[PDB]
Length: 68
Image 1 (cartoon, rainbow, N blue to C red):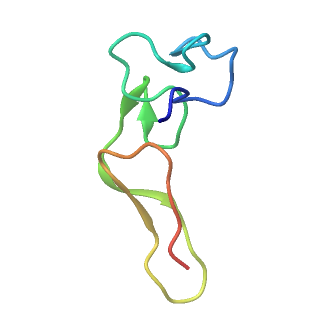
Image 2: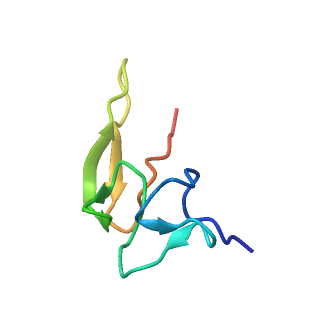
């Protein structure tokens, strides 16, 4: 059970007591969080080096994950 959508308690987007988005904001902190909203998928959230696939937001994700 996750009750903290954010790690910073001083964040206004996510309630401090419930560490979660209080309003209709999608995310309080993240690379795909534009205006506390989910940016769009296919977003180069991270650029890899070498010869693989860069990191692209999934549209419904806020924290850009990794692959290699």
